[PDB]
Image: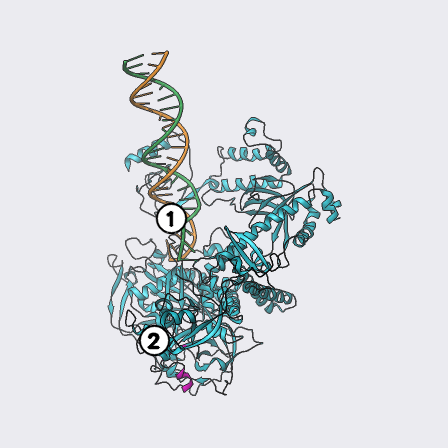
Chain colours: A cyan, B orange, C green
Amino acid sequence: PTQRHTYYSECDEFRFIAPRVLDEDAPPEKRAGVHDGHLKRAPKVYCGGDERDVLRVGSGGFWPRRSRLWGGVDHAPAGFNPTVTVFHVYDILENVEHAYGMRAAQFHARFMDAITPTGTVITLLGLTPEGHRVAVHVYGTRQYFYMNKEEVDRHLQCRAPRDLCERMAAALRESPGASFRGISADHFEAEVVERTDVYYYETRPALFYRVYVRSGRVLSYLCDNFCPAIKKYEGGVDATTRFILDNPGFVTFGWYRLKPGRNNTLAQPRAPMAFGTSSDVEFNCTADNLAIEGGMSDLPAYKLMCFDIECKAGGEDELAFPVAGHPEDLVIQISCLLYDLSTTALEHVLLFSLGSCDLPESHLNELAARGLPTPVVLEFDSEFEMLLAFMTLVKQYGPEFVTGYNIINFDWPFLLAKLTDIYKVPLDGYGRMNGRGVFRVWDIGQSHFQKRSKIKVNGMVNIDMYGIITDKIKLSSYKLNAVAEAVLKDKKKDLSYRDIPAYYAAGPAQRGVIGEYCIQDSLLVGQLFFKFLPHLELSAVARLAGINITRTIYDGQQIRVFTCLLRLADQKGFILPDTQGRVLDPTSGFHVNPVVVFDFASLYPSIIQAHNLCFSTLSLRADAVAHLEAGKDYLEIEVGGRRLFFVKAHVRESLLSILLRDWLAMRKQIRSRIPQSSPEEAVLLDKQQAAIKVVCNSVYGFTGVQHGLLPCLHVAATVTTIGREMLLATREYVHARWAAFEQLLADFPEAADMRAPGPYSMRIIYGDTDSIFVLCRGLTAAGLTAVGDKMASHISRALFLPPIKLECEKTFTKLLLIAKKKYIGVIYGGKMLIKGVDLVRKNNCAFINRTSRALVDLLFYDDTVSGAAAALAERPAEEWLARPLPEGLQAFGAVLVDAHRRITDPERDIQDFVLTAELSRHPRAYTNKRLAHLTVYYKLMARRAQVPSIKDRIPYVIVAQTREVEETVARLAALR
DNA sequence: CGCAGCCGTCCAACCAACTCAAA
DNA sequence: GGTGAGTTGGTTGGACGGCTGCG
Ligand SMILES: [Ca+2]
C-alpha cells in the first residue's frame, strides 16, 4: 500500500502467557501460576471444534467484519464500486499529508498542490445510507493566525508580507532541534487585513498580518517560539475548526452531499491501495465539493460495541486487584456485544475466553427465549492470542461507537497496558486509520481513590455508561448491579471477583458460568445505553458547538463556547488573542408558615444579555466613554474595587449577548415543536433543546476560568456582582412594597381568600446564588402557589430588564433551614424534598437508618411535632436547658425511647444492628489493630480462635462488657 | 494551712483503614 | 485539572484540675 498498515495482519511469534490450571491431568504442583515464554506459531482461535488463525481473513470467520482491506489485500467483491451521493459524518480527523509521500497515489493535481510540500487534510468519517463505510479527505484548509502590523514592522523591520514569510521561515530553520527542514517562505502566505482586538470598547481597528500556515505543528512552534514579544491571535485554532467555520452551514456530525466545485471539479475516488482508513470507499475533495444535505436527520446503520473484560490475579494473592504490568495477572474473558445503533437490535454476542468454556444450557435457553443471538464462544490457549483477536475484531468490524461500564477507567487502560507493556503491539493502526492514528489513554490527574481517565481513538467514539449515569441519576452506589436494580428495575445475577479464581480453576463448565455472568453484564450495559441514548446528546452538542463528538466528550466546556464565539467574533471583524502562559444568610430553624421559592430563570445568562456584558463592551478607563452619556449609553459598576464601564447595546451589542439571544431563540423554536412532533422526532428535539441548555449555562464559567481559552475575570466578576445586587433588590422590593397585607391585596385581589389566621408578614429567610425563599406568615399555602407567579411577574417588571425573569418554583408547607444549601421541606403536593443532607448513612446499620427517617418523617408529617418544633425558635438554645420542652415534642421523644428499648430487649432482631467490613489484608496487627472486624475474625469476640474466610465481609455487632467477652478478647490478646 | 508536684482526665489533631469500584 | 479521597475511629499529646504530700 501507499501508506504502511501498522496493525497486525501477519504474526508468526508471540509471548505465550497462560495459566497452568488449563493443562489437563497436571499434578497439583504444576497446576499453579502461569506459563510465560515465547512460542513460534500463528495466533489461533477455536470455535465449536473448528480452528482458524486469528489474522486469517476469508470465508468461515468466527466474528463479523466490515473491512474492505486486510493488510493491503482488497477483499471486496469483484468490480465493487458503490456510487456515493450523500453520506453521514460522525467524526473528523486532521492529518498532515506530504505531496512527496502521496506521489505514488493517483491523486489529481488540485489535491497535490494543497499538500505541496505539506498540508493539513481533514478526513470526514461516515456511512452512506446503504451502510458503506466512507472516508472523504478534504484538501485546502490552511490554518491561520494574526499579528499586529505596526508591532511586527517595528520589531523585525519587515516592509512587505513576503519579508515576514522569510522571517518565520528563518525562525523555523534555526529551531533548537532539527524539527523543521525543507522550509521556504512559500510554506507561508501573509496578507494585511484590518481587524479589532476583541478586548475593550476603546480599542481601535488596526492593520494585522494574517499569516496562513500549512501545518498545525509549524503553527504550534511559531505560536510559542517566534517573536514572543508580539501578541498572537487565534494561533490555537485547529484546522477542523477553520474548516467548519470558513464554510457556512457545515457541521461536525450530520448528513452531507458530494457536489460539483466552483470550476465544475468533482470528488475523486481513491484507489484501494491509497486508502488512509478501514473504509469501503474513499474520496479526495475540496470544501466547495461539499454541501449539507438538509432534510436528512435519521442516523445511519452505525454499529455499537458494548464490551467488558474479566481479569484473574495470578500472583502471591489470587484475590488481590489485578495489575496490568504484572505478566501473570491475566485478562481471562471478554464479552463483546455488537448492536446496530440505528435499529437498536443486538446483532452479535461474542465471548472471548482464555481456556475452553462451555456456556450453560440455562443461559443459552434464556437468550433464545428473549429473541437474542446465540453467543459465539471464541477459545484461546494464551492471553496474547485473545487480546490480539479482540483487537483484530475492533479493527475489522470497526465499531463507530464503543461503550461499557468503567471501560475508560479500567477495561481499556488494562487492555492497552497489556498490549503495549507486556506485549509490544503498536496501537496506532487499530483505530479507523491504517497507521499513525491516535490510540491513547491518559490519567486525568491527582485523584487517588477515584482513578479517572480519558481515551482518544481515531474514528471510534468511546462512551462510558459509568460517566453517563453518574452525570444523570442520583444513586447510593454506582455498581452496575445497583444501577440495573435502580434504572432497569432488573434483578440480574452476581458472581464475586472472589469466586472467579475458584470457578476458573474447576473446568470448562465453570469457566462457562464466568462467561454467562460476563455476557449478562454487557447486556445490562447495552440496555442502559439504549435507554439513555447518550450518543444523541453528544451528537446534539457536537452539532451546536461546531466541534467533533470526540472533543465533545473528552475536552472541557470552554471549547464549546470558544468555537461559537469565534464564529460570531469573525462575522463582526474581531479577533481573539491567544492567552499567555450577606443579609441573605439563613438563620437556621423550622418554619410551619408556607415558604415560596422565587428563582431566576438562567440568572447568569440573562444578566449577560440584560447588561450587555462582553469583552468588547467593557472598558476600564473613563476616557473610553467620556463622549457617551452616563446611565443612557453605559453602565458604571464598581467590581472588585475597580470602576468598570459597559456600553449599552445600542452603542455596541455584546458578542456573549448575541450568542445567548440566538440560542434561547432556538430553544424556544424547538420546544414549540415538541408537542406536535412524532415520537421519533420528540426524542431528537428533546436532545437538541437539552444541548442548547448546557451550552448557554457554560458561558458564565467560560469567562471566569483564569488561564482558560479567552478569560475575562471582569465580566465574570460583574455577572456575580449584579447577581448579588439583584437578590438584595428583590429582598428590598418584597419588604418595602408588601410590608402590609393591604398592599399585597391592592396588587393581587386574590389575597382576600388566601388570608390565614394570625399576623401577616412576608420576609426573605434564605437567598441562594439565584433563588430567594420568602416566608409567608398569615397566608394559606393553597392560593399562595398561584399568587407567587404574579408576584414574580410584578417584581420582574418593577425591577430588572427584559431578558431577566424571576419565577415562582414551589411552595414548601414546612421547611427546616439547616445551613447554606442544606434544608429539608415538604412541598404543597405532599412530597418531601431533602437538599444537602443524607438521612441514611452508609456506615450505619439498618436500625439507625430507619430510626433516623422515623424522627425526620415525624417532624414533617405530625403537625403536633411540627408546631412544637416551631415553638423551639421562640427562644435561644440554652434557655430550653432550664425550661420544660414545648408540648408536642413528646411524640418525637417517644421514637427515641422506643428505639432505645429495642436495643436492650430480648427478641432483638440482631440482623438490624449488624455493622460490616471486608478484612481484605492479612488478619494481624497493622497499625490501628482494634478494627472490630479483625477482633471478630482473629481475636474473635464470641467464639473459637479463627474464622474461615479472609477476603469477604465480616458481619459484626457490638456487645456489653460481661466478664466473658472480656476474658475471651483479653486471653485472645495473649494467644495472638 | 499553704504551696508544689504528680497523676488523671478530657479534648484535639493526625493517621490509618474502608469503601467502591474496576477484578 | 488546580482541590483530596470523605470518613471515621483510635491513639497520642497537652492542658487543666484535683488531691496528696511535704514543709
Ligand atoms: Ca468494565
Q: Earlier in the sequence, mark 1 or mark 2?
A: 2
Q: Quarter of the image containing the C terminus of chain A?
A: top left
x, y percentage for residue A501?
34, 56
Residue A430 visible in the displayed image: no
Question: Image height check: is A47 above or below A854?
Answer: below
Which label number is shown at residue A169?
Answer: 2
The residue that mark 1 highlights is A952
Quarter-of-image position of residue A405 = bottom left
Q: Is ligand 1 closer than 8 angstroms to the Cβ of mark 1? A: no
Q: Magenta part of the protein: which range?
A: A104-120
For the residues beneath circles 1 and 2, the answer to whether they share a chain is yes
Q: Nearer the viewer, mark 1 or mark 2?
A: 2
Q: Is residue A259 magenta?
A: no
For the residue labelled by badge 2, is the local secondary structure a helix, a strand or a loop?
A: helix
State which image quarter holds ligand 1. bottom left
Q: Is residue A114 magenta?
A: yes
Residue A6 visible in the displayed image: yes
Q: Residues within 10 Å of mark 1 (few under 14, many from 20)?
A: few
Q: Amino acid at mark 1?
A: Asp
